[PDB]
Amino acid sequence: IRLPAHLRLQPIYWSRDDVAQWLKWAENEFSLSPIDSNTFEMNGKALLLLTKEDFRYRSPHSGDELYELLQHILKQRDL
Ligand SMILES: [Cl-]
Ligand SMILES: [Mg+2]
Ligand SMILES: [Mg+2]
Image 1 (tube, rainbow, N blue to C red):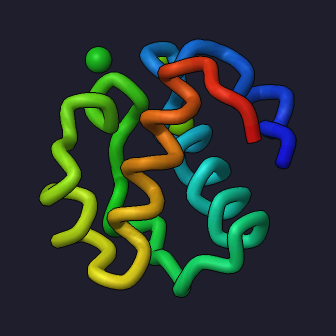
Image 2: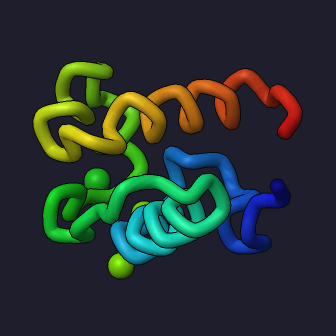
């Protein structure tokens, strides 16, 4: 479980393309239910404004995990 290099930047500087790459990494690394990138068409600054409920409406089957993954990155936790 190692973050892609470009995603090692603080998330507030993440592009919308970075967000898409994060979704792909997460899906593969944690074997999540498939996520459509069109459901998170936003940059990192916007992504950080989302609540857990917001993630779940965009990805009913993977939203919760995605939110908790982002929380772990923000907390600089390990993994
Ligand atoms: Cl902006
Ligand atoms: Mg930017
Ligand atoms: Mg972009």
